[PDB]
Length: 47
Length: 89
Image (tube, rainbow over all chains, first blue to last red; front, top):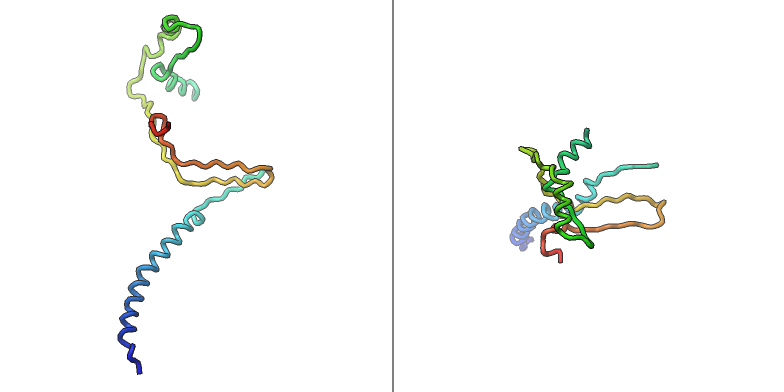
């Protein structure tokens, strides 16, 4: 019924293994670029 | 007192240069320097602390938004090397 069964889970392995590399990395890329906003400071100085 | 202390701290001979340019002669200027300037570092400090620490340069931005002003002023810069570096030329 499911001949692909074994290849799929070998791929599936690779998907979690790769995802476990890329996820943290891409997340870190976004934080880097968003740094500038996250730590920005404001001040109001009206007359 | 803040002023007198800043003065004493800084207006000390070895950090001063008496300069001139024109129809003068070096000896006259040297004579005058000796006549009117001798007696500044007749002291000279023990542990004082006149050293300059290097200054951290930071990649940053300061934006003072004011839409009431008719034109924008903007100034960008990277870190330069300093007076001594030949790269300046």
